[PDB]
Amino acid sequence: AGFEGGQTPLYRRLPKFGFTSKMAMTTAEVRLSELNKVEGDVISVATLK
Amino acid sequence: KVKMKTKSGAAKRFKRTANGFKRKQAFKSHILTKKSSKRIRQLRGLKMVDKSDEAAVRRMCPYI
Amino acid sequence: AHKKAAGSSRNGRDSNPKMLGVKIFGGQAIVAGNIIVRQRGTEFHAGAGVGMGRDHTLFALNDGVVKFATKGKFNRRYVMVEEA
RNA sequence: GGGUUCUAACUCAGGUAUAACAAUACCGAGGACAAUGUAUGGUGGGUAGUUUGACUGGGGCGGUCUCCUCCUAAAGAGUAACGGAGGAGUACGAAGGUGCGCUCAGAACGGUCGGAAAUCGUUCAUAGAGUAUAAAGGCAAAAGCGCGCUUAACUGCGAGACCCACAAGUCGAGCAGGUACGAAAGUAGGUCUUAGUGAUCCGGUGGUUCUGUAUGGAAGGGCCAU
RNA sequence: AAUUCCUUGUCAGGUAAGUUCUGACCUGCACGAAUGGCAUAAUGAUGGCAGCGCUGUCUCCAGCAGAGACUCAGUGAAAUCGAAAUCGCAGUGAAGAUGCUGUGUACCCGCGGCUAGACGGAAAGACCCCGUGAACCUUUACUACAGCUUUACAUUGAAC
RNA sequence: UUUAUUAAAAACACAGCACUCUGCAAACACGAAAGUGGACGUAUAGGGUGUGAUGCCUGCCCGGUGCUGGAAGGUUAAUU
RNA sequence: GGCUCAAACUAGGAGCCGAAGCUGCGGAUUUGAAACUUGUUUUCAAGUGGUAGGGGAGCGUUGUGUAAGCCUGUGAAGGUGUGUCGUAAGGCAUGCUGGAGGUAUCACAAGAGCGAAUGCUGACGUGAGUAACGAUAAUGCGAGUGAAAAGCUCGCACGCCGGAAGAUCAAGGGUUCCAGUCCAACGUUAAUCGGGGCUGGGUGAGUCGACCCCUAAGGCGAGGCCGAAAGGCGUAGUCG
RNA sequence: AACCGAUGCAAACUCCGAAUACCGAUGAGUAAUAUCCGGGAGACACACGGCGGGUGCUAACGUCCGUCGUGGAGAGG
RNA sequence: CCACUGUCGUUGAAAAGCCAGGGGAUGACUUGUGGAUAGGGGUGAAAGGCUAAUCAAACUCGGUGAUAGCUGGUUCUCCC
RNA sequence: UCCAAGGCUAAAUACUCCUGACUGACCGAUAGUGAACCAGUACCGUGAGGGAAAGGCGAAAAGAACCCCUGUGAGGGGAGUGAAAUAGAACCUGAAACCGUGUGCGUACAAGCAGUAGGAGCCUCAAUUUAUUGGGGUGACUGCGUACCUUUUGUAUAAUGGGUCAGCGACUUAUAUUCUGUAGCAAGGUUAACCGUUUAGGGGAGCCGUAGGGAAACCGAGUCUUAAUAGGGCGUCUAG
RNA sequence: ACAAGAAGCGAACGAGGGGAAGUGAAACAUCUCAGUACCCUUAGGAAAAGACAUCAAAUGAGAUUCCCCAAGUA
């Protein structure tokens, strides 16, 4: 994986870009169709857990 | 346990999209005075990894 | 190497192909922006409905049918896009 | 800020005792040197680890390696040879834009120096010239040659195509903003076109609210430009 | 010339005839003075050339003796080996044929010889090339290190 | 003397010659150091290098690279 | 081979031969097509050379459950023939041999299939009854014993060594030394013989040697010095 | 030297200029088509016979291209 | 004690010998016994010689199933 | 948030020279330990070290008294034992290579991968009213026909490999991931370690799916770029 | 000059002192191999570690060790 026989591989002719965010890994997106698994009427972060 | 290793340098240049991967374009780091302003403008931004090349990207980045 | 008359004559280089020529021939349907002729100089001239690029490239300004004709007092080769 | 001296650290592979080697004591000789530890510059095939390309009518030697133009190339494209010929690794704030205006090379005739040819006048004269730069293809609406004003050698883009394994490369009407020239319709996103070029990584610089490891910053990073 | 390519240089000697030898010439491709120059008695299982003696080295081989070879009795290997009912020629053909074509010849099987072929046996060619192979060696290749050396600090102090 | 087992030689050694180093805890060598050799020696000695009895001798070049000596100037580490 | 009004050449004409081509007949198979509809059936159409390679369907072998089953001394596995069946891998049956195990069916798991790797181990071929039988110092004959004598014992003769091929040791070996007995293997042949097998015997020291006392080179080395550790060196000594 | 008139030649000459080939349109019939997406490859030493050439000597079972057929991987006559 | 020449031998009597000759043979001699130097090390009158029939880096074990874009081989059957 | 320069501290964790109990879709004598056997042996090496081969009579030795040939030998034939003695100690079974003996046919005038398609004759069995078929063996004569593997553009190739036989010998295993098939559930699916009186049951931590855009903040069927609500990029309108 | 210990051997596992190269990077030096092989010291049925001069940033938790995730993520 990552070898073309000698020409600089595609993952090295192109530049690295962007940075990883720590916030993105602790922010979860919740769908309206998943709410049937909640017990009760309150929808909070602790209740989604 | 023993897991497949991501190509950690190929993950810094390819990002998962819905139906494929995206990437930056080359020829934009240095010597930019001689390039027409169309090149500076259309070499700027995202493209999609080619259909030809995205089997390699799938083998290099198995987890994205 | 008796008669010793041989010897190096270094002329073994050439340039890459340029893929010039007619891209869309007469009577064909064409859409605006389609390149008709890639050329050096004006071997063909831009008639009605055909634009001309800085490369001397002839392209369709509007949809229709591409047509070739020799017109004018210079007997020039013209390419036109007839609205058909 | 340098030298002289001293002895007390330290040294003795010096003498006298200690059976012997060593150590110790004293005497003697040096002495803040020498020597050693850390750091540092030099030297260092003494030794180690390695590298030292490919194409190629075998290899070596020589030549070549990227780009452009012509032919080979078989009237679409493409097409090889250590096949035949040449160029490029630039230039220009005008040699770009626009508006306006103009037409060349030569030959002959006449005319001071002055001729074969300088400058002037006349008649023929679709380019036998020019086009910054090789060649090919173009060029009168001149793309050739002058003048005035200028900065479109813009910014965000771009329907649609050519070419293409990819990465790249090429052309592009139209739209928005801000202009330049023109009385205006308009033209202008560099130059008649095709060579004048080099990915990523890394590092620098001009900007930017994007991030900012408890929090506010900052460092660092990201994005845009170079 | 242990050096000289051209080259068997040229001239002299030696031989009937001498690319070698000896003497000389100097036109030293490309000698030369302690990686010593030129000689040198003696020494050398040293190199070259020339003689006497002597000879089966040879003309040109002959005879003879012993040990094998050959026969019998006893013991009993070897390498090799796809399988063989294993001929010549001229062709053909992965380009030099026992095996294919055409043709010629040839009754079956031993023994003693022989080595022209079986591209005969033996050793995955050592020559040549290739492999981003190896080793060892060299250096003003690169990068290190040992060793040697420089200075600062420490062991390390006092006075003028 | 030598390539035990295809090379015995013109190769190596050799007495002799020269240069150079070394003042003694010598230079130099083994070693990680202690400890050794050099040497229970001491510059007529010891080491390294070249040459190689003897006879006649051994010319010129210090530009390069070494080696030895010198420090006016330039540059120059750690450190501060 | 042979061929001359051809069996040559040119121009025509008519027959015929000639392939795994085409057709005829029988059978299999891939894909698609109308339906009792999963091969439930009858057909039809177009196909079915094949390396690298891709796809599909199966055979056999060892083991597990099925199986405290079923088969088997009225003969298991294996071996060796024969017949028969299937497109094949292969199945079934059975004669003989054998003498104690085997395994239907369906799943499941593999040390699951060999002709090649100058493959590995064992066995056995060819060469071939061929080369050779190990210094050219040499043997002949008469008796004896014996199953058998060129080779053993005895005898006469002959030849060889004799600064050894004779004697004494050290080293090394270890019973090979002597006798009786045997001859399978070993001895490059035979063997009654032997350094072979088997069974007994044999080596007697104050003076020969070792041990012992002493030390050389060189080791080890209370303490001692040095070194990450291991260890290196070294004095007195102690070995040698 | 030119200029006129006859007369030849040229890959890098063209006042000209096919056949084919290529790019389109329309239309029948025939055909186990074309295209796109994904799983698995193998191959990237080719050879000869034609045709058009370069190179060589219009030499080579030579070499390098284009194009077709066969072999490769194909028996049979 | 050596090893200069030749024949033989080359599946040898012998993994270096025999035979006929050859060299040194009081010396830088030959030899017995014991000891020392150990692998990038030793030793070398120097041939890269020798260091247990092994030498341009011994042998044994281990890392180790080193790696090998190379060569060889790769085992039942049928259908497309 | 916690107080270094004082010292301790069980369990859950790692392992097997071993002792016991038990187990195996582990091997079965070329396997399994190198070693089923007098094996770390023989043997090789100065040494460190390397390192084999080699199992089976029979239920019970009942292991063959005695006789005969031979050398009081080997070996055998009788007798006897035994169910079996081509189970007789080299002993269960006894394959192949390889070597003999017997019978039938062919073969000494004919040129080659040794076969194949025909085919006369002969020999031998079973039927049959008696040479007529059928089965088996042989193969005079005719046609065609240059092994196999590997590697190659291309091999009978005089290119590689194999003397033969027998036995062994090469795509595995663990985990991750992707696609396909199949099964269960299905906008949901599924637990892992663990506990467990252990293939159950529990354990929801976690993972995948259900939303994307953007470097990111952020927004979200949208989002990014932009001055732009324009244009364009990437998404949207289920099955996991 | 008197008593008590130690010595040496023997599987693996632990702790500690030293520490490669083949290999991979399709070369190779940073890097990898790997703190592995090996050498050396030494213990116990285990060893080590262990009670916060530790995390966390939530509504806070509360020594060490080991397993599944987090995650092939940062």
Image: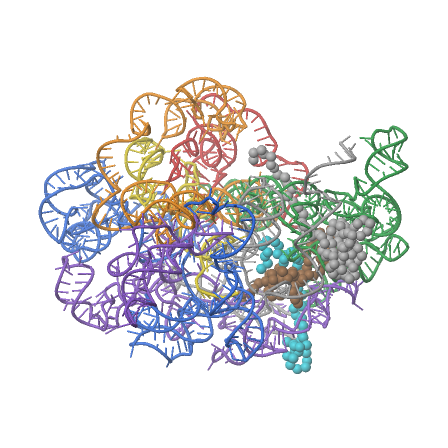
Chain colours: A cyan, B brown, D green, E orange, F red, G blue, I yellow, J purple
In the rendered picture of this protein, how many numbered marks are placed on residues? 0
Location of residue D211 in the rendering, given as x and y in whole percent from the top left corner: 70, 65
Q: Is residue C29 visible?
A: yes
Rendered image quadrant of residue G92: bottom left
Residue most extreme to the bottom:
A40
In the image, taking residue D194 as reference, residue G201 lies left or right, namely left
> Which of F25/D203 is in front?
D203
> Which of G40/D96 is in front?
G40
Q: In this view, does C9 lie above or below J160?
A: above
Q: Residue at x 82, y 49 (%)?
A: C73
Rendered image quadrant of residue G44: bottom right
Rendered image quadrant of residue J129: bottom left
Location of residue G33 in the rendering, given as x and y in whole percent from the top left corner: 58, 73
Q: In which quarter of the image is the N terminus of chain C?
A: top right
> Which of B47/J219 is in front?
B47
Location of residue D186 in the rendering, given as x and y in whole percent from the top left corner: 84, 56
> Which of E79/J221 is in front?
E79
Q: Quadrant of the C terminus of chain C?
A: bottom right
Location of residue E60 in the rendering, given as x and y in whole percent from the top left corner: 31, 29
In the image, taking residue G83 as reference, residue D77 lies left or right, namely right
Q: Residue at x 79, y 49 (%)?
A: C75
Q: Can residue C54 be seen in this view?
A: no
In the image, taking residue E110 as reference, residue F68 lies left or right, namely right
Q: Which residue is drawn at 74% across and 49% down?
A: C40
In the image, taking residue D86 as reference, residue D140 lies left or right, namely right
Q: Residue at x 68, y 77 (%)?
A: A32
